[PDB]
Length: 327
Ligand SMILES: O=c1ccn([C@@H]2O[C@H](COP(=O)(O)OP(=O)(O)O)[C@@H](O)[C@H]2O)c(=O)[nH]1
Image (cartoon, rainbow, N blue to C red):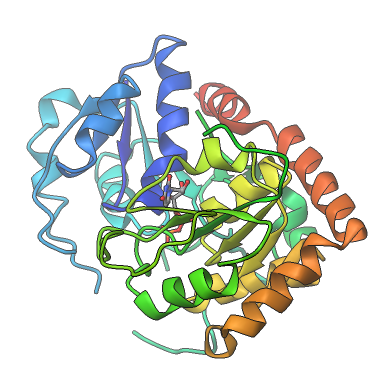
């Protein structure tokens, strides 16, 4: 019986679901402490949905007591997301084995998530640490040892004869209507076919004169669109970045917060795409960026290499195999 404890967010829940499924198809009782918006997703994966009140969209550790209502169903191993500190604490109260999942960058002794910002121990890595990226993409991957398992992404339309482009700012920092308007004007009369995810904050009808080569929706099946996409204007979330590599889709990254800037720079230094800072996003800079990487055959070759790295990392299957072997 394995307990999954995670914060309420797609960027943290999505790579977990494929891991839930794999564990369920090997005969483990996967319980999962989430909220309500995520309960149907964990249960489609075959997990035990344990709805709990969060009332939050710093530490806010008023959830451990809410997830303690189940001492009768005490777990044999707790799996918690790095930001989900409740699971880390809970797992130390029962002295139960515990494993850390890294939906973003892994942190060790040489690298820590922080832009020189001091703000008042548990961040030390556990015995096993599953990171949802290949080793080659982890920052300072040479300083990481065998307690970190880089399994890569954890994953579970008619097109035409023209290049297909996907535009999405993720599921959190998507409230930026000026960007969407600039994208429409940037590729209004182009040969590109655009599929743009606008978020639940904007309404497709609101936008005026929607071009015939554009398709705007509040949400979109990213994975399905990435299998036929030729380019992906993204925001630097780890999931979207790793899903683009899995699909072999080069990137234009426009980050909205610090971590996404790390990834944006990471993508740029690996030659997997272009980092276009938010403050430089214009109609012309969007056109120049898309034109720069879409005609760069060498950059595409490096994207194909990172695709192979992503495949070989193992995915949800190798992650579940590592959890079972961890006993
Ligand atoms: O229209 C959309 C927008 C996002 N996603 C998914 O939502 C996640 C985005 O998380 P990411 O870590 O990339 O950024 P965040 O949304 O947490 O900022 C990924 O799994 C995407 O595949 C999706 O399926 N459709």
